[PDB]
Image: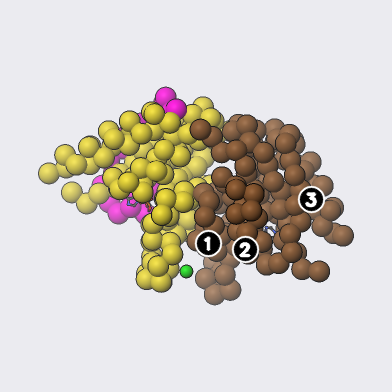
Chain colours: A yellow, B brown
Amino acid sequence: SAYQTVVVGTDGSDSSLRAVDRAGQIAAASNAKLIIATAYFPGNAPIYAILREANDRAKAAGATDIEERPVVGAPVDALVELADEVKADLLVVGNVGLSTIAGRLLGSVPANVARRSKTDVLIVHTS
Amino acid sequence: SAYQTVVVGTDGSDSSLRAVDRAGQIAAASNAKLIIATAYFPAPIYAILREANDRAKAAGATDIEERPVVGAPVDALVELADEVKADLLVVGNVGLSTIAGRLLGSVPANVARRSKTDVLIVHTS
Ligand SMILES: Nc1ncnc2c1ncn2[C@@H]1O[C@@H]2COP(=O)(O)O[C@H]2[C@H]1O
Ligand SMILES: Nc1ncnc2c1ncn2[C@@H]1O[C@@H]2COP(=O)(O)O[C@H]2[C@H]1O
Ligand SMILES: [Cl-]
Ligand SMILES: [Cl-]
């Protein structure tokens, strides 16, 4: 059953843009819609700079159906909620934060996304 | 450039066979080889792997290897992915969102953290 809708979270980090490269490849192969999301607490010119570069990276990896979503709020909430809202088949994040003791105990975006998601989660090895 | 070598872990559970189903489909769509791995301690095992092969085929995959590996699930999956130069490791989600899991460890969380490859955690339960 092919992925139809893939959501990828980027904060503009090089690590995260690697997560976008991969989501873009997976989307192009599944023939899926890719949704690039960037969560932020709000001026807001850099959020759209992040989304256009992510778009360019995803398009270079093959994706052709790409949507950009600037989302107001915290990263975990914004990605999980977005994924429920668009009925995403897959949610993609990088792995920054997964290995520190403080991230394991206090939280990180990939770990909390993995725990909270009701869909498949791809954790791209970006660091 | 796609994923070319996909590893999926199964213990024979129905939940882990849904992870095999998804890995099969990804392998098909990517044009990759699928490796089906079952970690154990010292054969139920070939029964398990034959079911998994059947499911993976049903899913579109054709280039399949069965690989039984000795040891604990996380160690065996992570070492195998290293040895076979896996581009993607696929596991199901049992234990991931439970406190028992934070306390005893879960396969998916430990794999996500310790693998050196992309990890797809399938929402199998
Ligand atoms: N502000 C954000 N918006 C969307 N996703 C984010 C944000 N911050 C962190 N993430 C995700 O968490 C990931 C942690 O590792 P990466 O930097 O490789 O990639 C990151 C993104 O996928
Ligand atoms: N002995 C094992 N061999 C390989 N993979 C395992 C083993 N035990 C658990 N797993 C993996 O961890 C996942 C936990 O959820 P599932 O049962 O959906 O799918 C399981 C497998 O992918
Ligand atoms: Cl560690
Ligand atoms: Cl719990």
The correct choice, above or below, for B49 with respect to A4 in the image is below
In the displayed structure, does residue A115 sit left or right of residue A71?
right
| Residue type at tag 1 | Arg
- Dot 2: few (<14), some (14–19), or many (≥20) neighbours within 10 Å? many
Q: Residue at x 22, y 51 (%)?
A: A41
Chain containing mark 2: B
Q: What residue did someone put label 1 on?
A: B114
Residue A121 visible in the current orientation: no
Q: Give the range drawn in magenta.
A: A62-79
**Residue B49: assigned label:** 3
Dot 2 and dot 1 residues touching (CB under 8 Å): yes
- Answer left or right for A47 relative to B79: left
Q: Are marks 2 and 1 on the same chain?
A: yes
Q: What element carries label 3?
A: helix
Lower sequence index among marks 2 and 1: 2
Q: Residue A112 appears in which quarter of the rendering?
A: bottom left
Q: Is mark 1 within 8 Å of ligand 3?
A: yes
Which chain does the numbered disc 3 sit on?
B
Q: How far apart are the alpha carbons under marks 2 and 1? A: 8 Å
Classify mark 3: residues with Cα within 10 Å, few (<14), some (14-19) or many (20+).
many
Give the number of the mark in front: 1 or 3. Answer: 1
Quadrant location, the N terminus of chain A: top right
List the residue tagged with mark 2: B74
Q: Does the magenta stretch include residue A24?
A: no
Please provide percent x and percent y for residue B114: 53, 61
